[PDB]
Image (cartoon, rainbow, N blue to C red; front, top):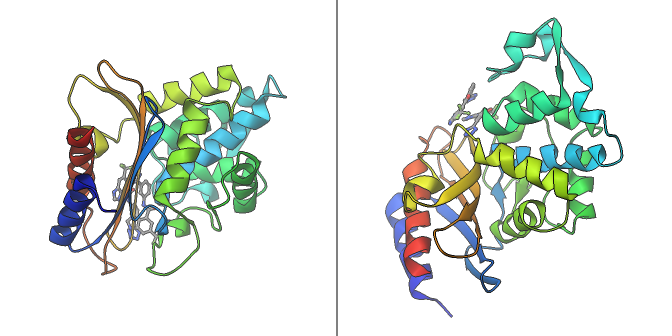
Length: 263
Ligand SMILES: O=C(Nc1cccc(-c2nn[nH]n2)c1)c1cc(C(F)(F)F)cc2[nH]cnc12
Ligand SMILES: O=C(Nc1cccc(-c2nn[nH]n2)c1)c1cc(C(F)(F)F)cc2[nH]cnc12
């Protein structure tokens, strides 16, 4: 069937000229609302959540791992490194790298997380370990954001990512202290006010991770604590036909508004 919410998401998508993917899980009843929920989309920096979570999982058996220093060299800087560039010729701890990747979207920090896991395939291996058979990370930063239509590299589906984000932030994929740390990091994101959050009532609490890439790819994944109800998990992915297309965070806000209105 096609629901009223799905029809509105299709109208939004048509007006936008692009391709929109949405997955909601309402933990009040475990129900799901999906739009293109099983189509693949480039994750871009939303993949930083899986990398940080994989390091958190490693830290469950190494109490000092998050305090471990990682050298930052001039050659490690890539295209967007607002935190890491302050530490060139010095070090950052794995906690600092996780916070920078998640809250500032630092690409050098992400590359250090990937390297700690043995490469992109180590991130994929963690996804499989927590029951996500769909996620794949194939490249490092910045090339994982090429976002080429039809390219399976560095993609997932909205359904899979919503399920994984629920397990990581509200479920038991991580230990309790690690889950709390991930939630704290997401709630402190600096980059999210124009994306999912912009479509939701201001009283609601949001933790999210944004992403963007070529093909005007504009993404956000969020855990949401609405006023007076159980938490929601919402993924909004958007990509466009031309390589140079402009970002469209407003489309993500509009999708979130349609979802909220449909609860
Ligand atoms: O850093 C960014 N973009 C960037 C930097 C360097 C190079 C290129 C690029 N390379 N080839 N095409 N574009 C792109 C960026 C950062 C952020 C952030 F994290 F919120 F600050 C949001 C964004 N939305 C679209 N782009 C961004
Ligand atoms: O790295 C990139 N973008 C970036 C970096 C850091 C943070 C964010 C971001 N975080 N939350 N929203 N956007 C985005 C990027 C890379 C590439 C390329 F060609 F693959 F290298 C093309 C791009 N077109 C627009 N952005 C890009």
